[PDB]
Each structure stands twice: as C-alpha cells, then as structure tokens.
Amino acid sequence: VSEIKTLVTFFGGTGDLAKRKLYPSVFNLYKKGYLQKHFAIVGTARQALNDDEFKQLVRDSIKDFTDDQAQAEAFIEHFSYRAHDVTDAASYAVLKEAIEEAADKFDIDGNRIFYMSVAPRFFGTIAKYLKSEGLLADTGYNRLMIEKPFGTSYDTAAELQNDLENAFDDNQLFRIDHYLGKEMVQNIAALRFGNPIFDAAWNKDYIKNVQVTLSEVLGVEERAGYYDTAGALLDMIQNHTMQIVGWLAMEKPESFTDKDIRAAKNAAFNALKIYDEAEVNKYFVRAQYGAGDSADFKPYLEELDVPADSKNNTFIAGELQFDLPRWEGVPFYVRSGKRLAAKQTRVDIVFKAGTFNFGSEQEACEAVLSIIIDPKGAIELKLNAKSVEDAFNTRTIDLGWTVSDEDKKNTPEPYERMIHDTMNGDGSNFADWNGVSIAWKFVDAISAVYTADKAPLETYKSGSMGPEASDKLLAANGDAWVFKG
Amino acid sequence: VSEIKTLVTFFGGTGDLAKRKLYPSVFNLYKKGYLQKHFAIVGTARQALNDDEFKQLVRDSIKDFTDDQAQAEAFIEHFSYRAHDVTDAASYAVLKEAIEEAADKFDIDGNRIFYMSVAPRFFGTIAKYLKSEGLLADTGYNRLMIEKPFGTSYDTAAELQNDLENAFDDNQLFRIDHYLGKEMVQNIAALRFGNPIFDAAWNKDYIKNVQVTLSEVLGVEERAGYYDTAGALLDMIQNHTMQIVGWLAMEKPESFTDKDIRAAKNAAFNALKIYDEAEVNKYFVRAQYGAGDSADFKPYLEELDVPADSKNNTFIAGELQFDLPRWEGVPFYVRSGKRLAAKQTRVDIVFKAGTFNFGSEQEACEAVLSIIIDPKGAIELKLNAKSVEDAFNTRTIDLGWTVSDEDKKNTPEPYERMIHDTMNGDGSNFADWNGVSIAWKFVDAISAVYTADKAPLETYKSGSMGPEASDKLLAANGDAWVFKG
Ligand SMILES: NC(=O)c1ccc[n+]([C@@H]2O[C@H](COP(=O)([O-])OP(=O)(O)OC[C@H]3O[C@@H](n4cnc5c(N)ncnc54)[C@H](OP(=O)(O)O)[C@@H]3O)[C@@H](O)[C@H]2O)c1
Ligand SMILES: NC(=O)c1ccc[n+]([C@@H]2O[C@H](COP(=O)([O-])OP(=O)(O)OC[C@H]3O[C@@H](n4cnc5c(N)ncnc54)[C@H](OP(=O)(O)O)[C@@H]3O)[C@@H](O)[C@H]2O)c1
C-alpha cells in the first residue's frame, strides 16, 4: 500500500476522545501500512507531561489493539508532546518548535493536519493563532479537523467560519460528523449511480416520498445539561439528518470527485425551502416524551436536572421540500427522537404504485427501497409479486441483504475513515460551508418559532414511534411512515 | 366460494395419469368448495367396469388425500363410468347416453369439459366424433383439454388443429403444458407489470440479454424409446422453453384479460426470426452427453435401447431474436439438457452495466434479475454496491427472496390449476394456436438441419453445464451464462 507522509497535531491530546477514539484509529492506519516511516504525531494540552509520559498514555490507549508488541512500540516512537495553553499566543512558539523538531526527526515536508479535540469555544482562537504565530506549513497541505458542533445557529457558525477562513480555505476544513463516515451511508451513491434501473428512477416520476428515520430507545440520561438547550432539532436534525438527506437529494454529478459531489449536493441544498412561522406549524412537529408502560420510563420533565418548565423537543418530525425539477412535488419526511420504539437509522424510498390493472382484488401497492444504516447494515426491496391464491392477485415480497460478519470485520470505524480521508485530502464524505450554512438557515427558522412558543409542543408515550401529529403530517399528502417499529 | 357447475368426461379414465394426477386434483377443487352439488365426472375407457368398480378405482386414487371419510364418499358419489372404444363411432351413442344421465341426476345445464388422457393418435379422432355423434352440449360451453404432445412437427400439428377445429374454436382448446401451470412462471407478469421500475426497464435500453435454463441431472433413463426420436429439442425446447419465453418477450397488454395477454404474446411470437441452414449453424448448438467422472455416468450411446448410430440431441442451446422495437439487438439465450450440473428451471435477466465513472478500480458490473422456478421458488436481484475497502470501489450484492413453507403448502399442483382454469374459461396460462404454430415453424427449421446432418453434433462431460460451444455462442455478443452450476 502507498505511504502517507503527514504530521498530525492533536489539540486536547490528553482528552477522553483522543485516548478512546483518535489514537487507536491512527494506530489502525499504521497496522494497514498507510503510515510507515515519514509521519509524526504531536500531542498537546495544558497538563505538564514529558515525551515519555505521553508515550505511556498512548501505549495504554492502544493496549487493547496490540498483537505484536514490537509493532506497537515502533508506532509509539513516532509520538511527542508539548504542554501548551491555547489562549496564550506566546505559548504557541513552544508548540511551533515541537512541530518543527518532529518534522526533522522523521523528515516530513509540510503536510500538516491539526485536530481540535477541545471545547468549541476555542475553535476560532486556535485557528487564528496557527496563522499569526506561524504553525502552518509553507510546503504541502494544511488541514483542520473541527469537532462538533460547528456553531449553534447560523450567526455563530458564520462567525466561526469567518475566524477559520483567516488561516484556511473551505476545502481545507474537515468538519466531523460521524454519521457521514458510516459505511452504509456511503453505499447510497453506489446503489443509485451504479445501477441504471435505480439511477433512472431517482426522480419525481417514480418516487412518491423519501423517509429518513433516526430513532433511539434511550432517554436524555445524564446528558440533561447539554440536551435541554439543544433538543432533537440541534442534536440530530441540523447535523446528521440534513447531511444524510444531502446524499439522497443531490443531482447526478459530472464525475465522482469530491468537488463534483459537493456541487451536486449544493444544487439540492440551494433549492431547499426555508419555512416561515405558518409553514413551520404546517410542516413540522415538536414533541417531548411522556411516561412509559412501566415506572423507569419516566417523562422528560421528571428526568434529572430537567427544569420543570422545559419545553425542549426530544422528538422532531417534518417535511422538506426541494425546488428542483427532479424533486417537484416529492416530500422528504424526516424524524428523530428519544424513547422511541427502536434504535434505528434508516432511509425508506417509497415508489409510486403502478397503474396497471390486473383486475385483481388487491392491486399493485408501492414498492419500497430501504437502507438500514444502524444497528446493522441491511438493504431491502419490497416488490409486488403474485399471491399464493387460486385467483390471480398481488402481494408484496421482500428481497433482502445483510452485511456479513466478514464485512463487519473489515469495515473501518468512522473515525479511522475520517482521519484517513483527511490525510487523502478527500472532501466527499464531509459537509462543506454551503451545505452547513443552509442547514443552519433552515433550522434557525424553526428554532425561532419554538423559542417564541409560536407552535404547539406535542407529547408521546415512551416506546411509541411518536405523537399522532407525526402521522397526520404524512397523511396530508396520502403517505405513511414505512417503519412502524 | 362460488360454485362451478360442470360435467367433465375423462377419456382414458383408467389410465395412470387419471388415477395419479387427475382425480386427486379434482378432489382438491371439491375440498376447497369450488365443486359442490351440480357437477359430475364421467370416466371412460375400453375396460368393462360398472359404476361401482369405477367408484372404487377413484376411491383408491384419492385415498392418500382423505381426512374426512364422509367428504371422500360424497365426492365419489358424483362419478359414473361407461366402457367405450374411441375408434368405434357407433359406440359413441353409449357414452352420449351416460353423459346425459349424469347431467340429469346432478342437474347440469351444458358446461362440458372433455379431457383426453389417451394416446396422441386418438386426439383428432375423438374430437371429430364428439361433433358428429352429438356429445357436445347445446347449452353453456364445450371445452377440450388436449394432453401432450400437440404434434411432432408443424405439419402434424397443423393437421391436428384442423381436425380439432371441426368441433371447437381455438378459444375452447386447452393444450396441457405443466410448466405454464407452475406458480413461479405466473409471477413473471406480476413482477414486470406490477412494479414501474421493472416495467419501464423491460426493453433494449436497459436489458443486455435474457437467459432461460431448463437443466436436469438425470439421463435418458428407461425413456430411450421415446427420447431418441424427440431429443431436448422436441421434449424441452419446442414446448416448455418457447412458452416461458412467450411470457418474457410479450408486449405490455392493454389489460390483463386472457385475450389481451395472448395478443401481446403473439406480437412477440410473430416477430421471432426463423433460421435458415446458415443461421442454425451460427445460433444453435446440439450436443449429446459423454462419460461422467465415475462409471455409472455412461455416455448416451451406451444407454439401454440407444442405437449405437444415434445422433440425438440430449442438449440444445441457442439464441433467439425478436424483430420488435423493444427487443432490437437483445439476444434471448435458451438451453436445456440432460446430465448437466444441476436440476434447475430459471430465468436470468442481465441488465446493461451503467456508464457512470466512480474512478474506482472495479467499475459497475451488470445487475441481474433471477427467477428460479424449479426446484424451489426464488427471486434474486444482483445489484452494484460499495465494497468494504478503504478506497471507494464497487462490488455486487444479492438481494434474495425464497418461497416460505406456508407458500409451498398453499400452492396448487400444476394439474389442479390447469383443470380449474379450464372450468373458468381462462386461457391466459395456455398457449394458443398462433404461439404453438410459430414454435413449431421455428423448431422445424432447426430439425431439418439436424436430420440432414448439416450441423455438427457436440459432446459434453456428464455433470458439466454443456459443451464449450454453448459458451462460444454467448461470447460472440460479449455475454456469458449467469448460472454456472
Ligand atoms: N469524547 C466523545 O465521545 C466526543 C464525542 C463527540 C464529540 N466530542 C468533541 O470532542 C471535543 C473534546 O472531547 P473530549 O471528550 O475528548 O473532552 P475532554 O476530556 O474534556 O478533553 C479536553 C481536552 O482539552 C484540553 N484543554 C483544556 N483547556 C485547554 C486549554 N485552555 N488549552 C489547551 N488545551 C486545553 C484538556 O487538557 P488539559 O485539561 O490538560 O489542558 C483535554 O485534553 C469536543 O469538541 C467534543 O464536543 C467528543
Ligand atoms: N402419466 C404421465 O405422467 C403423463 C405425463 C405427461 C403426459 N401424459 C399424457 O397423458 C396421456 C395418457 O397418459 P397415461 O400415462 O395415463 O397412459 P396409459 O396408462 O397408457 O392410459 C391409457 C388410457 O387410454 C385408454 N384406452 C386405450 N385405448 C383406447 C381406445 N382404443 N379407446 C378408448 N380408451 C382407450 C386405456 O384404457 P383401456 O386400455 O381400458 O381402454 C387407458 O385408460 C398421453 O397423451 C400421455 O402423453 C401422461
């Protein structure tokens, strides 16, 4: 396999994410032979540790992924550390020095990746100092990996983007969204464009509606502190759901290059309808989970640290509309919520029923293409066939495929994939500025109605798939949620 | 369920087919409540039996399908018999009498079905006498069920048709072909017309080639006496294969009525290309099985009662061409043979690979829709998806569906279905004159080249899928057999 020559700096190197997810992911790239001799990893945080102590931290982090002791040690030898406060400009001179020493020791010409595994408030600060204090390489590339979230409204995101653009171009920004790094999400484009029978049918003349579900069975848990201010709207819709929808609604690209894929996705995003107060009440539904059918399934307001006057949404369902010729009249239904009937991330594409008359009692129903992303990768195609009756009649049958154990074994973790894509300079599995800003504009419009309490807050029994208003939404267009639980 | 009022006469009533297949099939229709009070079954043959003895014959025939003794006896009470020689005109007066007595006893107004379970040489004779001797009902319908074969060449079939048309119209003729009475064969039209994504793709712009396989693992066995003069050509191709192809190549009908289905099938049959000597050598392959990989798999010439100078075909493979806009440039490959790798009756529809460039090492292959009819009903769709690799690449995955045990339990035997369809007057699962005559014209053209030895006779190892010439045939158009064994 070909060698990747790169120098990666991990801000928040002693963090939980760094030791649980980042280091093991990088180790994997080394095991596969992508990282060989010309690469270095510089960790940093305020904690005063020397190179040996940091190496031991990394050693303990990759412990459970070690087979060959020699292999582990050869990898660990590529790490170095430097204590540093991100708010102290002068202190950046010390980190600059460590970076240059590492590049010398391992002979790396530029090719720097900066990973921000720190609190969101530091994002803009760090980027500006990388530029002003001279940490950016003058050779090769310079890429920034920004952890979530990327803003909390269009305004803040716009501000962050502005600060980031001081030192980087948008094509150098890699916003983390682990859902886009999921293997099955990447199968959408393959199924669509790789098969003419689907490619030709991916439009208003064959599709009736598209449904995206991101259900969870757990509740707010110990995360009340954050969740109460975010809700399903900011925690699941704005980011994960919107980006999955981007893959589904995109135009057919000129080629499969990241640049062309983004242009095709943006054509869709730019045609998305932004709702006013009236439209929000008509096309969206917000809810909060009530009691379950036992006692441990307590209502959201009775959860720990939840203000008894919280009107936070633990569920969102809504209809999206694209003003593009291929999607004219095709609603895109989305829904995500806590304490629902099942944990599942799926896409259901409902095809219009055919008008051929068999003269049978039961006529042709709608065919459905389902792509289950979580918990296990699956693809199902519900088609119309002949029923086993004496008289000719139709029925639906399901053609299915499931990921094999061998498949599961070879599938890279989402973080490995994302770091690897960044080293490659491949932006196809990453949201760009345009897609993110539009996602924010769309969501802000809804938020405004919610914080101003200009829309009802619904309730639903824990364990159900949501309030009846969710079904009322689809019924208005003669549609129904495919996944019932 | 609604009651069927009918009087059925079984010529060859004491025959093997009558007691093994016919009577139990009719009994089933009674168990389901289709046959109630107004129906009678008149059996006939030369053997001198009285009504009691025939009833006992029927009793022993349905023995293994009895649960309720009372039910069995109520059914048996509807049977009567009359000794009769089909070559003796005068003797028909005696059968006429028995038929009219049965109609009185059970109050049946016309609605007569005559089943010919006798030797083929009697077919024309029986029909002519039914007319001249007055056995046809003057009220209701009169339908004739002709067992196989329907001729041995276009000439003989044309002669038989002429004799049959003395007393019946073609719409009253029901030619038996148990393959058309198979549940899965009837699922073709449902899959195609019931699903717009397939309906719209069932033409030259999406399909590369269609393949029909009717393989068997057994050899000529004890059937040398008949087989040696027929071959795979007359035994499997002319009848079974041609009619399955009819379902596949038909135009889209105006409605799903038997009349419209036949008109749509005939549009295809009429556009079928009849081959000359040159084309036969170029588009067809005849072979005979050689030795296997043990000793019990002896060559065809070493089979019992096989003339050491036999050039009989135990395998046929060929390309069919339809001169219709929807099939322009689309070859239909067919193959059937003995001592092949596996017993299987299937249809494989190869879709043209897409031209979208992923920039991957492995580009999009051809999608395949497979319909397995025998031994177990199955439907598979091979599609292009993303491979589980670090770099984006494509692979094919299989979406499958299999008939459930409950399905198998409810599926009517082919004979039950055929008799039931005849009582209903439904000709959709039956070949009409036009389809049969064209099938004969097509086959005769090939036969002529074979009996005149103007084409090579190939050889193949028992257990293989046929001679290499079979593969050479598809390779000429850049195609390959999907089912490898
Ligand atoms: N872990 C998860 O599962 C997860 C999942 C999704 C998203 N994320 C995101 O990843 C980022 C951090 O996650 P985490 O779980 O790893 O958090 P964490 O345990 O709190 O780690 C914070 C890191 O930042 C360092 N730090 C604090 N203040 C600093 C400063 N003033 N200057 C320099 N370094 C400073 C800390 O080291 P010192 O205290 O020694 O300075 C520590 O290494 C956040 O953006 C979070 O949203 C995490
Ligand atoms: N059984 C199978 O699996 C099978 C499968 C496919 C097709 N078929 C077709 O079904 C037909 C017969 O099959 P089979 O297996 O049932 O044969 P079979 O046992 O030979 O029966 C022949 C019947 O014809 C009667 N018969 C003979 N000569 C007659 C005459 N001169 N007048 C009146 N009746 C006469 C016989 O009764 P008498 O001798 O007492 O007159 C007997 O009942 C054939 O066309 C065959 O091709 C059979």
Image (spheres, coloured by chain):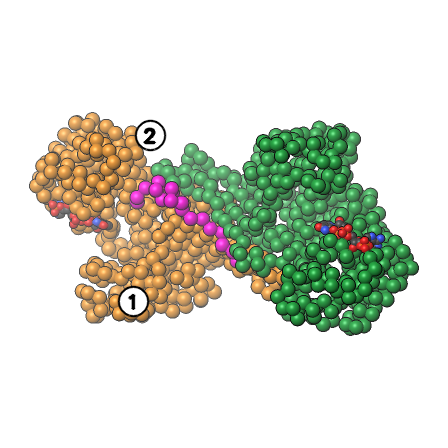
Chain colours: A orange, B green
Q: Which residue is mark 2?
A: A1
Kindly identify which chain the residue marked by label 1 belongs to.
A
Front residue (pair B163, A269): B163
Q: Is residue B9 above or below residue B337?
A: below
Please tell me if label 2 and label 1 are on a single chain.
Answer: yes
Amino acid carrying mark 2 in the image: Val
Instruction: Kindly identify the amino acid type of the residue bearing the numbered disc 1.
Output: Tyr
Q: Quadrant of the C terminus of chain B?
A: top right
Asked which secondary structure carries label 1, the reply is strand
Residue A242 visible? The answer is no
Distance Cα–Cα, label 2 vs label 1: 50 Å
* Helix, strand or loop for disc 2: loop
Who's the residue at 43% across and 64% down the image? A474
Q: Nearer the viewer, residue B173 or A150?
A: B173
In the picture, measured across the screen, residue A395 lies left or right of residue B446, that is left
Give the magenta range: A396-414
Who's the residue at 30% across and 56% down the image?
A236
